[PDB]
Length: 252
DNA sequence: AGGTAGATCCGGAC
DNA sequence: GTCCGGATCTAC
Ligand SMILES: [Zn+2]
Image 1 (cartoon, rainbow, N blue to C red):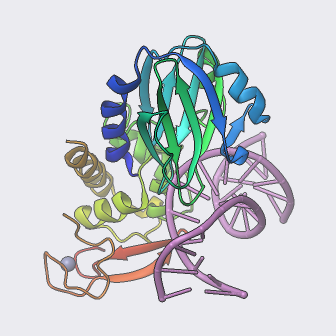
Image 2: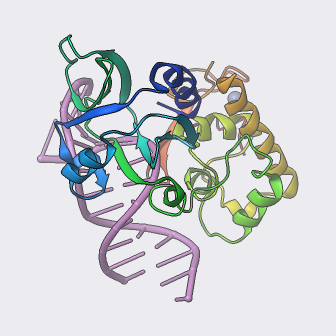
């Protein structure tokens, strides 16, 4: 799920788990657990804690319990569901939190690619994976000045910069390509080559693109098809190690 | 020093 | 057999 989808999950999951107390934690693929390194320690420490809140930082969900925060990343295909302990689990379920009320919060992922870290609440923000995470793209902390400061300092392309989680939190491949299209900027441009005007426009489009989604595609996945704005066929290349889509007329 | 590329994890689709 | 997302860890 992309950032807007993580926000929807955050909003919808909260009322379904708040105030429930963990009675067991069952782990079917231990590699999902990244901290504590022992998945037995992970399961043991959560028992007896009640869910108090649910926050989002980039694409991370932060489950707030009594003493601990559980930091979860779903990557592309991870999903959470709340359901009865009496009913069979869905395929690819890797972690289940059992509540004292007979309900369960289940984590499933065909790709088996997500991560979970648990730390004392007060430590979560200064440890992996949240440590060093850049500002929320919809917050005033993400400003053109901040984007411009990072851009001038680097030899990397503008796409590489935007994909950097220390620059801006959880701006995925799809939103990078769409925002660069809307800003009229080629994804392979050196970030240091952007004018003040271009940086301002890019920040504007980034906020608008994410903002609209949190609250429909021009280029992503549309290679070989006409640009919706000018009719030029959309092209795909590799930039920053990623599938990268652009209109060669609209973007420069 | 520290910026930045490369390796790493996974499995459905090609 | 190779490819590919995100984000972190390793090493140039
Ligand atoms: Zn175009």
